Image (cartoon, coloured by chain):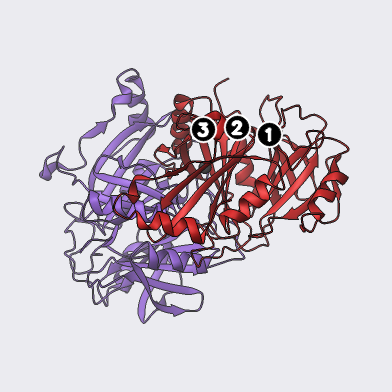
Chain colours: A purple, B red
Amino acid sequence: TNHITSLHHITICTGTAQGDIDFFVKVMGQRFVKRTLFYDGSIPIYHLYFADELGTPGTVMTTFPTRRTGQKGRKGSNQFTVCTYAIPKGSLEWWIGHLNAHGIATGEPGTRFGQRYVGFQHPDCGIDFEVLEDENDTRQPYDSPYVPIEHAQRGFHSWTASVRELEDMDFFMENCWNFEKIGEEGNRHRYRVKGTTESGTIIDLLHEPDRRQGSWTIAEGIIHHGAFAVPDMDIQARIKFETEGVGFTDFSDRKNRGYFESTYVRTPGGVMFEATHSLGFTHDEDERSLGMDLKVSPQFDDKKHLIEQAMEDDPIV
Amino acid sequence: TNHITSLHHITICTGTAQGDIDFFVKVMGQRFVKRTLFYDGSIPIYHLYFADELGTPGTVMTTFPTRRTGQKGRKGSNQFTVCTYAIPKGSLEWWIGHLNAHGIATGEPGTRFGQRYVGFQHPDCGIDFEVLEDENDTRQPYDSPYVPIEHAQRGFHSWTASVRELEDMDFFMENCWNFEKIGEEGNRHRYRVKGTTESGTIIDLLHEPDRRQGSWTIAEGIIHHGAFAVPDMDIQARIKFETEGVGFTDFSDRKNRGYFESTYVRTPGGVMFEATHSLGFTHDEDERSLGMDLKVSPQFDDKKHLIEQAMEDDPIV
Ligand SMILES: [Fe+3]
Ligand SMILES: [Fe+3]
């Protein structure tokens, strides 16, 4: 195949680094697979990665703990609003259990397209999550402590985008982005990668024309963008060219973000999309010891003291 | 100075090429300064340029006659909606006159921030224009036939953008784009290049949260983007970096568009902005004979017959 294939990673702005470890590792049972430090013009900021065992597309979660900038983002309508993990069928109560046990309030369990889910928030920034019973998801769960292999989530089921302009967003998914509407209930419209069988291939659009646009900038409490897996850099370039061709001339240059190749476009629904080529997480760290070594970026050669600043104010354990 | 300095060009999708010549040259009294042919994946499409004598920033108008694609764009709320020329004071009636004479209906003359204007449409696609009496505009009018030098427009006064999200758009103008709010009347908020004295430095934002978003894609009847003059490619790159830094990672690669260097970003108001470096219109054509030679692009080497297709169905006289 030669177009975007599935979801790849999602990227959110959170509070403290320890907040995320406590949540993504100790609560969700994901492996801490990479940690990096970059300089954002003012202060050092972590870029943390969380996935299954080896950072496979459709399970990767990336975070910028951004409590140390004053910026607090506004939940709103032109952004991703909810990230949804797939858990095995029958596992909801255990999750409600091992979530409440951790002090994380959960909400009214529901059904969405026939499958059960419950919502809850990242304790340290407010971002919205769900666990959803997918009997059709056969992906290998990562075996951590914290969560037994019987009940482990096995990657992302779907992401939910709030959008004010639905018609033109639908056009973009079908014509530029290799998705097709596969369902609709209420104001929720569900799109799936054309052809696919794998899980982690679902984007739900919430039509909310009424609602004020959310924050687009890097600020605490927000999902900054969603990324989609593309087989290689050629398909990437082609998607960029044809998408520019129809008018989205804001398709970015290809950026190396460490462990993947990224191009960014602002869709007519107001949501940043990424077309991503995968680089792996092992090329600079031992498989057995992922997430232990802090990869600090070359901008710190002149200001090493800031590394020490990040380690104590945003401590990682 | 080392930031964006003024307006540069505006780029609109129109009907037929003859439509634009009849309008921009024969009605507005602008010089036809360049004409090019490119291939858009389906059909040949002109890219026409209209300005003062030598294509100076703040007077350049570019058009894609797009009647030959079926696509008809939707006027709406996340786009540029009105382009405004500056005419001398006392000249409004002559214009109302030489516009009506040409069959172009004009509307209720008005006053905006103390200055008089009248609206009217491109006869061949529907796009909205204004002439506005600016006694403070001292730029050299181009001396065409069609319009006497006494009454000639001397460039763009302002552009008017409709936007649903005003607050975050204001933030973007001040913090990334070197503009500052200088006035407000009703739902019109006026921004001007920080510091400037020159004319052609004004962007008016119309706050319209109620209104459905317009078309973003290349389609007849729409303004696709506005471009802003930047002194050189270094300032350009810096603006790209700092703007990406706060979250607009969709800032495009620098593209050579023939007669200028362009980078594109989708602002939080939903409007495409360009940071433009100028290349001039003479580097490939004689000053005395601008707009006479059709510069066809290298994509036509394999399909020369399409050049002949454009010349007769979109004839230029
Ligand atoms: Fe990304
Ligand atoms: Fe442009």
Q: Are marks 3 and 2 on the same chain?
A: yes
Task: Please report the residue visible at 72 percent of the width from the left and 34 percent of the height from the top.
Answer: B154
Q: CA distance from mark 1 to mark 2?
A: 8 Å
Quarter-of-image position of residue A307: top left
Q: x%, y% of residue A69?
A: 48, 35
What is the count of numbered marks? 3
Foreground residue, B49 or B285?
Answer: B285
Residue that numbered label 2 is attached to: B57
Q: Which mark is residue A237?
A: none
Disc 1 and disc 2 in contact, CB within 8 angstroms? yes
Chain letter of disc 1? B
Q: x%, y% of residue A141?
A: 19, 63
Q: x%, y% of residue A136?
A: 23, 76
Residue that numbered label 1 is attached to: B200
* Mark 1 Cβ inside 8 Å of ligand 2: no
Q: Nearer the viewer, mark 3 or mark 1?
A: 3
The kind of residue on which mark 3 rests is Phe
